[PDB]
Image 1 (cartoon, rainbow, N blue to C red):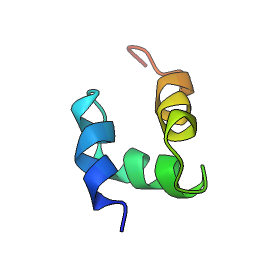
Image 2 (tube, one colour):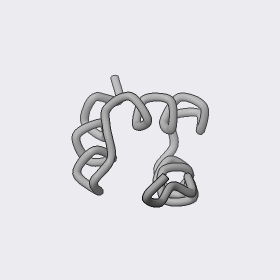
Image 3 (cartoon, rainbow, N blue to C red):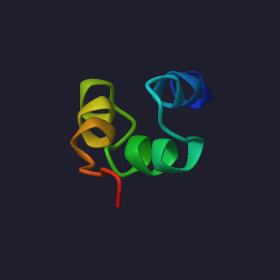
Length: 45
């Protein structure tokens, strides 16, 4: 499973949904998943 990284990805200030899709679309990687969630441009709006 990847549930281990889920709380990790979430711990960066994200959410288990954007996390899963950022760790499944990233082919369950590490530096890739982080890069996904951190590269997901999203401000006030």
